[PDB]
Length: 129
Image 1 (cartoon, one colour):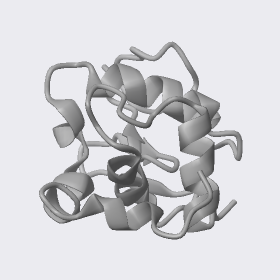
Image 2 (spheres, one colour):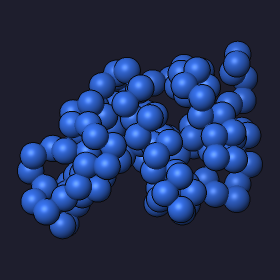
Image 3 (cartoon, helix red, strand yellow):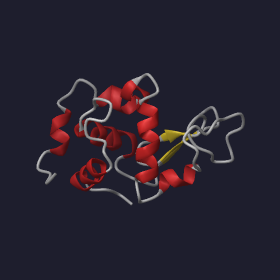
């Protein structure tokens, strides 16, 4: 599923991401935009054999089990296929663990390179939240 901007914003707000760990809703929407272009089915194969899954492009080397990444971990206790669901619950809950792992949202490269420091507030512009 490909989310609309405000549609995703509302869903993330519903799942408690607004101001979670000090990051406003705008940061999360911006992150999703540049990580996956709002596509829940997005996947990116990395050079080390791991894969990034879903709306927030969460990596299989540490966060989920895809059964095809040798020597990896599964800290979110979920199959990576759950991160490809149209229901963003799994991605959100795992993301909350990731952002609490000591590096804030810097864990998301796309967010760091295109969202951090900008007026992220513009990402929920015109939304009914």
